[PDB]
Amino acid sequence: FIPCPVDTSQVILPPHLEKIRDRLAENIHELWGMNKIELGWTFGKIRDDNKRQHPCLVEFSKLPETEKNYNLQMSTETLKTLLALGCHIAHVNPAAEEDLKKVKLPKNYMMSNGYKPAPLDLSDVKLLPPQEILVDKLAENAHNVWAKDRIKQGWTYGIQQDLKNKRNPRLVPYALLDERTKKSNRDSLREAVRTFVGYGYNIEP
Ligand SMILES: Nc1ncnc2c1ncn2[C@@H]1O[C@H](COP(=O)(O)OP(=O)(O)CP(=O)(O)O)[C@@H](O)[C@H]1O
Ligand SMILES: O=C1CN(/N=C/c2ncc(-c3ccc(Br)cc3)o2)C(=O)N1
Image (cartoon, rainbow, N blue to C red; front, side, top):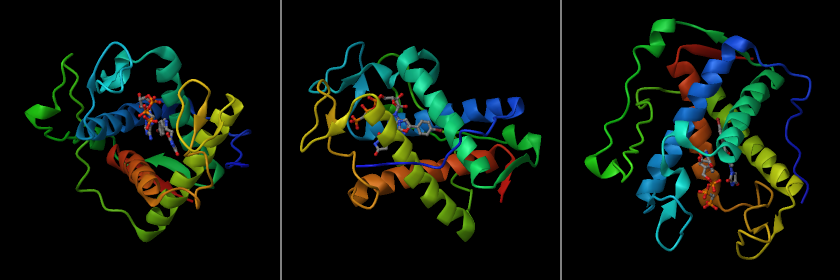
């Protein structure tokens, strides 16, 4: 398999966008954390799958650095992909970042070590058709960068998953992937673009 995403090599992130890059990394983690609780996952200091344990059930500020820093790199590369695709990222209203509310996660969405995700409540945020074809493209590219970075870490495909010999069945072309995983990814990058407009930024090629 040969994944190659958009080439962001020559793009430079502006320093004033390093904050929306971090806000985006927090929220996408909060969206990941919420759905993981819905899949029957709780907090724990050691990775026990049969016990529904995962250390990174804590808030974004408390993740280990080898895991936390990859999220901030994936956020940066998604921002650079927009600029590489010819989009200008501007700022529309700064008060939009203060007229931001978060979602009322029920009491069950409170974990053992006080971690309770609270993503931005962006259910009021509609997307134009051009923005739904861009989000669909963005989620496909996000798969290629994830696939190549694991291949560059030594990962190969396998019929079943192995967390030690680096094999994983999801390292396939985006058209080869199961539709359940595609949809999960397309939704996550949908909320990514929503976070930009939700924080008051504009995105037009
Ligand atoms: N699809 C995704 N979207 C956003 N963040 C993800 C992500 N997948 C993993 N992460 C990030 O990685 C951290 C969780 O560690 P990990 O990489 O092992 O995920 P995971 O255990 O769910 C993969 P698997 O589905 O195989 O179990 C979290 O902090 C999370 O933010
Ligand atoms: O097919 C797949 C694709 N994929 N995605 C890896 C995921 N890990 C971290 C992130 C991420 C995305 C956006 C932002 Br902003 C910040 C972090 O992407 C996976 O795990 N199997």
